[PDB]
Amino acid sequence: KETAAAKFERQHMDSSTSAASSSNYCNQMMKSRNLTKDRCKPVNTFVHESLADVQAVCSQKNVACKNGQTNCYQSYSTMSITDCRETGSSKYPNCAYKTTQANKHIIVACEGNPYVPVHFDASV
């Protein structure tokens, strides 16, 4: 709500493009969202759907988190997703990514207040 909803939006949201067809997306994005900062994560998923669209999921199909469970919700249909996948070997500022584009469904956890997604569980 104050750091979680921001945390999620930081990592997973990109509602400015309907998609992403190129490794350029991933490389710029990870950098942009300073996701390479200090230590760039191996793999990250960006949702190309309006933030509202994503919040909406908080009141869709109720599932089981890959941990505790419910408070986990699954997207009815298919979401425009972009997968960012590390590539460039070495453990330093050397971070390159490949841009894989899918159309999968999302599993999100939601801290309502109104509703705000805070943790992006599995991407299908």
Image: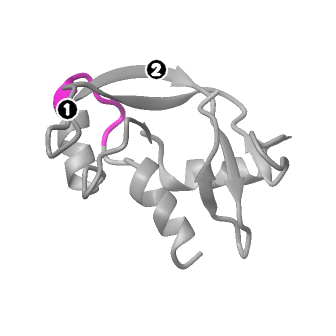
Q: Is residue 56 above or below residue 123?
A: below
Q: Secondary structure at mark 1?
A: loop
For the image shown, how many numbered marks are present on the structure? 2
Q: Is residue 65 magenta?
A: no
Q: Is residue 5 above or below residue 38?
A: below
Q: Which span is picked out in magenta? A: 17-24
Which residue is at 19% across, 37% downward? 95
Q: Quadrant of residue 30?
A: top left
Query: Can you give x and y, in whole percent of width and height, for residue 29 in the image?
Result: 25, 45
The residue sitting at the bottom extreme is 2
Quadrant containing the C terminus is top right
Which residue is at 30% across, 46% downward? 40
- Which amino acid, mark 2? Ala
- Which amino acid, mark 1? Ser
- Residue located beneath label 1 in the image: 90
Q: Secondary structure at mark 2?
A: strand
- Residue located beneath label 2 in the image: 102
Query: Can you give x and y, in whole percent of width and height, for residue 63 in the image?
Result: 84, 39
Quadrant containing the N terminus is bottom right
Q: Is residue 18 magenta?
A: yes
Which residue is at 25% across, 57% downward? 37
Which residue is at 74% across, 69% downward? 112
Q: Quadrant of residue 65?
A: top right
Q: Give the left or right position of residue 74, taking residue 124 as reference.
A: right
Between residue 43 and residue 61, name the one nearer to us: 43
Query: Can you give x and y, in whole percent of width and height, for residue 32 in the image?
Result: 21, 53
